[PDB]
Image: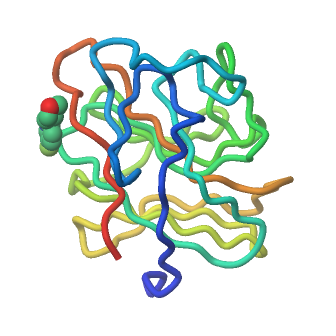
Amino acid sequence: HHHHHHMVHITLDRNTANSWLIISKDRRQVRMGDTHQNVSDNKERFSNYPMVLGAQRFSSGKMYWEVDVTQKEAWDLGVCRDSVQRKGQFSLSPENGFWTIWLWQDSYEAGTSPQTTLHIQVPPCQIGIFVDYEAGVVSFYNITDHGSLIYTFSECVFAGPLRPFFNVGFNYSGGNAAPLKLCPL
Ligand SMILES: Fc1ccc(NC2CCOCC2)nc1
């Protein structure tokens, strides 16, 4: 792919984070803490899951960024509507305002309803995410495998501003403590 030139500098929005997340000083890395991180509750925070949004909002154009997932057992990545539900249980689907892929139990799946099996021969250590607002496209790339395509959501009905979306996953196993990191341009 030749999307690298639409690179954008993404930072994480502390105020949207689940209360157990630890966001680095530069707002470029996030990981699961072993306890509540001593923040006040607010209506923006994801309550049920270890999720956080990027600060940037996109309503036009072409945008590209990269995320490091090295050594993680579970995570979700993509974009979502600014107005997604924050509290309680919900599925990751375009009907609920999410365009995502994930790793769970040694399989990769796209967040369609129902979910779609992905075919990845080289487990990725870094994921590239491309959004074309006008075209209604969200695409995912395997940076570890020379940029190979993972998945394309097309005919997307965004229906509002978009925000970068992250889930570090739970760490019940003790094998999923590693952070998500926004990779340099
Ligand atoms: F690839 C990695 C990177 C970090 C990590 N674990 C971190 C958990 C919290 O203490 C710092 C290290 N595991 C795998």
Residue ID at (74%, 36%)? 84
Residue 87 % position (x, y): 69, 18
* Residue 100, x across and y down, in percent: 55, 46
Residue 43, compared with residue 14, is above or below; it is above
**Rendered image quadrant of residue 41:** top right
Q: What colour scheme governs how the chains and residues are painted in the rendered image of this protein?
A: rainbow
Report the quarter where the N terminus lies: bottom left
Q: Quadrant of the C terminus?
A: bottom left
Q: Residue at x 61, y 26 (%)?
A: 45
Which of the four quarters of the rendered structure image does ligand 1 lie in? Answer: top left
Q: In this view of the protein, which residue sits in the foreground, 175 or 103?
A: 175
| Pick the front one: 136 or 67 | 67
Q: Nearer the viewer, residue 116 or 24?
A: 24
Residue 12's place in the image compared with 167, above or below, is below
- Residue 72 at x, y percent in the picture: 24, 37
Residue at 31% x, 64% y: name it: 183
Position of residue 167 relative to residue 162, above or below, is above
- Image location of residue 36, percent across then percent down: 40, 13
> Compared to 153, does 102 lie above or below?
above
Give the residue furthest to the right: 159
Residue at the image point whose x is 70% and y is 64% from the top:
58
Q: In the image, is 175 to the left or to the right of 143?
A: left
Can you tell which quarter of the image residue 24 is in?
top left
Numbered circles on residues, count: 0
